[PDB]
Image (spheres, coloured by chain):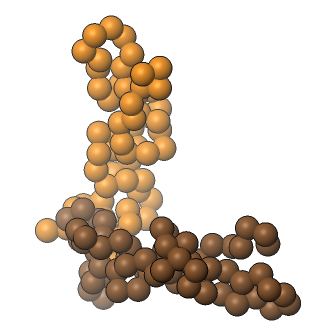
């Protein structure tokens, strides 16, 4: 198949869309900045969506 | 047209093992070697070169 977010002639997200897949992508758009994408095991340094990428970046306080 | 020969439409990324889809510094789905000349300048000796890590033609950083 082709994923519903993909323009397969360009190999980019279709016109009007942001992203294809990933923990911080939902329905071809980025999740809002600050959305929690993984809760920490010990204590309170969670990982959060950036608003501008589809990955879930590691908390910078570590 | 068809799906681009370099594209995996299931992922919307290059097929596994390939580098890139299109661009002046992509050929056959791979990055051209860094230093390949991608645009010769008019007036001077400042030409633009492929990076070996991206598929675009970067503006020479001296200008």
Q: Position of residue A2 (x, y in %)?
A: 20, 67
Q: Nearer the viewer, residue B50 or A38?
A: B50
Q: Quadrant of the N terminus of chain B?
A: bottom left
Q: Nearer the viewer, residue B63 or B1?
A: B63
Asked if residue A27 is positioned above or below residue B53 in the image, the reply reads above
Asked if residue A52 is positioned above or below residue A41 in the image, the reply reads below
Question: Number of callouts in the render?
Answer: 0
Asked if residue B55 is positioned above or below residue B47 in the image, the reply reads above
Q: Position of residue A32 (x, y in %)?
A: 44, 34
Q: Quadrant of the C terminus of chain B?
A: bottom right
- The quarter of the picture where residue A20 lies is bottom left
Chain in brown, by letter, is B
Query: Which residue reaches farthest left?
Result: A1
Q: Position of residue B17 (x, y in %)?
A: 25, 70
Please indicate whether residue B49 sits to the left or right of residue A42 in the image: right
Please report the residue visible at 65 percent of the width from the left and 87 percent of the height from the top: B39
Chain A palette colour:
orange
Query: Which residue reaches farthest top?
Result: A43
Query: Which residue reaches farthest right?
Result: B43
Q: Is residue B29 visible?
A: yes
Q: Nearer the viewer, residue A6 or B42?
A: B42
Please indicate whether residue B51 sits to the left or right of residue A41 in the image: right
Asked if residue A39 is positioned above or below residue B26 in the image, the reply reads above
């Amino acid at each position: 198949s082709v994923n519903p977010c993909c323009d397969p002639v360009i190999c980019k997200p279709r016109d009007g869309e942001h992203c294809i897949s990933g923990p911080c992508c939902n329905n071809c758009k980025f999740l809002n900045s600050g959305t929690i994408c993984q809760r920490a095991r010990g204590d309170g340094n969670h990982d959060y969506c950036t608003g501008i990428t589809t990955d879930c970046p590691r908390n910078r306080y570590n | 047209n068809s799906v681009n020969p370099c594209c995996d439409p299931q992922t919307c990324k290059p097929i596994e093992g390939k580098h890139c889809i299109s661009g002046p510094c992509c050929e056959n789905c791979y990055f051209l070697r860094s230093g390949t000349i991608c645009q010769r300048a008019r007036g001077d000796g400042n030409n633009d070169y492929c990076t070996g890590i991206t598929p675009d033609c970067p503006r020479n950083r001296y200008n």
